[PDB]
Amino acid sequence: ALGVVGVLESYIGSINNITKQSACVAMSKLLTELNSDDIKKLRDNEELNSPKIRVYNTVISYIESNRKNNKQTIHLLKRLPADVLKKTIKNTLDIHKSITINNELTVSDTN
Image (cartoon, rainbow, N blue to C red):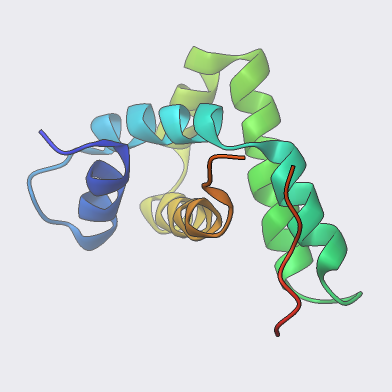
């Protein structure tokens, strides 16, 4: 029984017998845990027209959908084509690596 991140990574890679249902439940937990205010800091630090801006805004929208309608957002994730779900999860795992911390905080200067 892996944790949230391990379950999601397993689903992306089609290993450890993780089902789409378990992945979407775990994804909902990850979206709850992620701090959307910190993602907005990352987004605002991008140069304008950076393709990352759209990614950050997608994860931000999914956090808001998950916060309003938890179980419907899980169903929405289950309805997504597998390849679209996996891209959304991968982007969300990437943001998790960038913002998880015990904090107020700033954004790094390197590029």
